[PDB]
Image 1 (tube, rainbow, N blue to C red):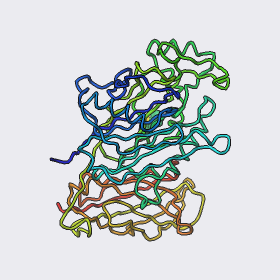
Image 2: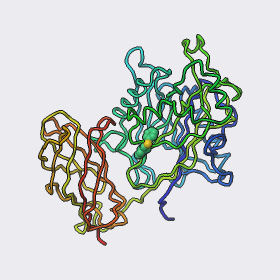
Image 3: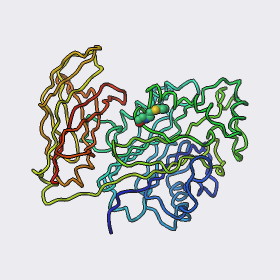
Image 4: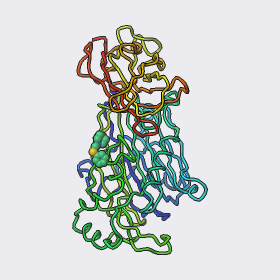
Length: 460
Ligand SMILES: c1ccc(SCCN2CCOCC2)cc1
């Protein structure tokens, strides 16, 4: 039975509005409704992994697991296995997988982050799950961010707190936050970004939605505008939105948006908005293709509609050679030439690099670089030809060309990372000097760049 080189992943996000679901929710898992929908000819084909994020979920874990498993069994005639379930207040994540994957999945982690302080601590935050699927690390975050049209900055702050403090994946990757720990990271939820248009324009917005004319609305979507200004979700991707706003509906129909201010809304307007979103970030040159992104039309218990997204995702096998794991393979090496970091810091300490990768027996620390001044004010840290030669555990190019090197640039004075990035070993050539590049981030914000050349030797 061969190991897969691709899997499909279903991501669902639904703010349930504190109401039990209706008796049938299969359209959600079938990617049917509005937007980029899944072909009817695929309806009986199970996804490999289903990741369900809820917000304002009134159900017990047991109650929701029984609904989800029975739903998928009706669709697919497969009894899915529960990989993980984690709940913070009314924010929940469930991961289900086909039974054949049970002995491909390991290192299952769960965590949560509570956002805000005092007042603003008590119902918003995130839950997450990570695990290994054979050689590939997968992370999943379901977040319920701060509500309200005039709180986009709070939402951006909630995002940074979640990516700093959510403790998922390999703890040995100590300089790296969740935005670097996974081959594939999916971040979804009721992110609560709004369409930023004047209140007086509510009926005009509704008109546009009825005409399926979303362009003048998406140009005011706060998540797209904040992302384009690099204020949030730097280096994540989202599929084009081709479904109507998923909030705020009158319950028990989808014929009406309920936008007007009420005591129950704190006298706030809720103009129609794309509150409910799926984003991803995968390591460079790994296969990931969004195959659906849309909303259901027939699940009407909540003031939100469920959102679905599905992905093809490249995976790798758990590789064994006669040498590594458990030793190095002398026929492999990774060399860095002419490398330098460009940092935005105003500080003057010496810096060194750390190289982390599951192709190495353990992480590698470089010598200190030589600091110079860039022509436009910047700090440039030069490593020249001084970086250590990296010794992979396995030299076979079918393994090594699928790997990645995480890089942290650390202060010699404090051993704190000033920037993190990732280099793919999926090169155009071996035994050939080739340019490499990564942006560097810290707490998910841009802090600099790392560039130079690589030379990769494999057994071929
Ligand atoms: C919002 C809207 C448009 C863009 S254009 C750049 C798109 N990507 C994103 C991440 O991958 C590289 C570039 C970005 C944010």
